[PDB]
Image: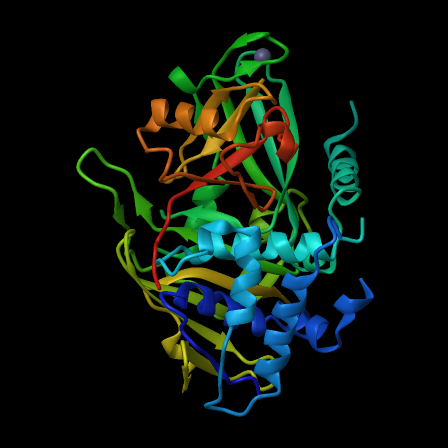
Length: 315
Length: 76
Ligand SMILES: [Zn+2]
């Protein structure tokens, strides 16, 4: 059933919101429930993956309106990320990043055409970082830097486990802003390695490998002389058929995603509340998780201006 | 070597660095450029958040790699 709520241990709604999103990440949940993790590290430590998996196993063997305590779990993520030792308000995406890095580390199994360069860079990355967690989240960006003087296009390939998107509004607009030709001029002029001097260049991202689970993180922040504030712009994201083919490095590479979870924030950059909306893998039905409270909702209520992290699964 | 930062609006800026430069040194350069205090910056690369006290080479950050700058929406 999987509708247990999580106890708020003291400003830990950022943590509970992300844990529900992961609980309803189908392949990640299954990995824990079949305890494939015991089968599978960067150090001697396994307690973070153990408590994370026991938390998921407890949520999925629980009855509605059970409340589960993530206390043991918190003790372990703190050791990876001391930022979380206290009970202060925190950012869900920062939490997600340290949590997945920790899980990953504990079960870590460890002149050419551009195409070929990318494929070789990828292998180099997997030679160092290769886990079931990565399997799910990891993708590869291509970045093309072209000198406007000599026309050389320098290409590099960076792994990613999520994308942090500027807000342009539609989600696609934000992806186009992320992937646009960026003109690097004036104080940002790069050195062209062929010209061997500073030149106006154009830099452009495309997606060389798409991940099985695509986490999109909306940069709801604005820096000004007058104030740092949160952007509460409504960003309209689809429930189904998010089609990212126009962003792919390769023409055909099809990449269509359906939403299954959202972490919501309400407030300013300095404080606020988190909840999650998540689609159950089993039933397809959506529920609102606001700590210990879990209520059904319709997918028509899922898009709101409070969405901050979007969890999509590849179709 | 040069690396890039994709900033809050999606603007990209260019930093000159060495692999042995500390993440704090990088945030100091971002601040010079964008005026965001370093304590407010979070930099993400290959899914890791870069931490003060580490260097670029600990994260295998290569020439022309891009770091992704985000702030925080604190909540709880
Ligand atoms: Zn050139």
